[PDB]
Amino acid sequence: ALYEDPPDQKTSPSGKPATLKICSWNVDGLRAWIKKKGLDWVKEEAPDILCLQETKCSENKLPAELQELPGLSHQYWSAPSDKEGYSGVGLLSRQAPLKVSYGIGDEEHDQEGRVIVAEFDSFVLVTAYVPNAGRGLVRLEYRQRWDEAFRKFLKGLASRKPLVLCGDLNVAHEEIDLRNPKGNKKNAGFTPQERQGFGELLQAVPLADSFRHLYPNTPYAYTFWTAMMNARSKNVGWRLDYFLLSHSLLPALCDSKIRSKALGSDHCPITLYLAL
DNA sequence: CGACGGATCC
DNA sequence: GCTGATGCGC
DNA sequence: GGATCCGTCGGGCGCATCAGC
Ligand SMILES: [Mn+2]
């Protein structure tokens, strides 16, 4: 029931060494995460690109430590427009992207600081903090509209350039992706509509779930544990955080990691190795 | 959203 | 202008 | 009585505003 992520596979299936290391982390409050030493872990992980979700922090209030990241110089941020203190995403990059945009090209879905798009030479990186359907499923209908628009946006992106989508997609795709599937069939994150949404995304773009592609039969691998129930200590969790890849990037896939041991949030980090 | 308790069936 | 109480969104 | 299925609900974070000093 407890889980230990296998060691880092650093070469591609054809032997090419990894050249790109991307780390994604819902930090449950950027300023608190930094207080709990989250950036010390980042320095030890040394990613080429760091995506952050649920920063809950406007660009004006970003801590100063973020300016002391010598290898993550190019920092892009997005915050909600209506009010402060919820959602928010960041993208920090060792090299400058050719182009950075925000949102998914749809007004209704572009107000809550949820999506950053960074275009590199040979691939485009999207990081996302997917809207929660809420206690009582009060936002379920909205989440279904989000799912369809996100899917159409990413399908268009992937048709122009190979795509990496990372971050908190806020859904456990299959029963293997959470510890309590039958008790959660009507809870945000595991409704049949959200799981069907995820499935259509995989098929329609198409995209491959990098972790599940490499470890199709591995249960108890989670990236989130609720903070109240001290569920983390007993590994009662959900896999909400993903790297989804264009099929053309699969021969470059070296590994997709779940950094279970890294503290600082109610999500743990995930790390992608690509041999580009 | 996991712990809990109630309801239904055996 | 400061702090605690309270509410929102996970 | 136990075993399966479900519906209810308390609890707690990181953040905000604001009413009270
Ligand atoms: Mn969260």
Image (cartoon, coloured by chain):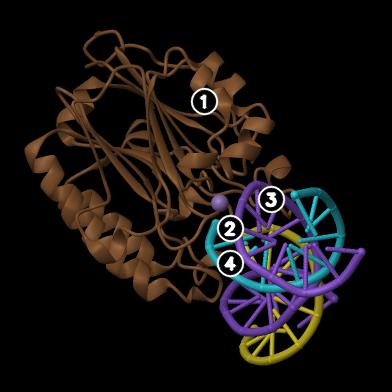
Chain colours: A brown, B yellow, C cyan, D purple
- Disc 2 under 8 Å from ligand 1? The reply is no
Disc 2 from disc 3: Cα separation: 16 Å
Q: Which mark is residue A183?
A: 4
**Front one among D1 and D13:** D13
CA–CA distance in space, label 1 to label 4:
40 Å
Numbered badge on residue A80: none
| Number of the front mark, 3 or 1 | 1
State yes or no: discs 3 and 1 in contact (Cβ < 8 Å).
no
Compare residues A226 and A63 and report the one nearer the observer: A63
Q: Quadrant of the C terminus of chain A?
A: top left
* Residue position marked by numbered label 2 in the rendering: A180
| Label pair 4/2, CB-CB below 8 angstroms | yes
Which chain does tag 3 point to? A
| Closer to the camera in the image, A47 or A200 | A47
Q: Is residue A183 visible?
A: yes
Badge 1 vs badge 2, beta-carbon distance below 8 Å:
no
Label 1 CB, ligand 1: below 8 Å?
no
**Residue A263 in view here:** no
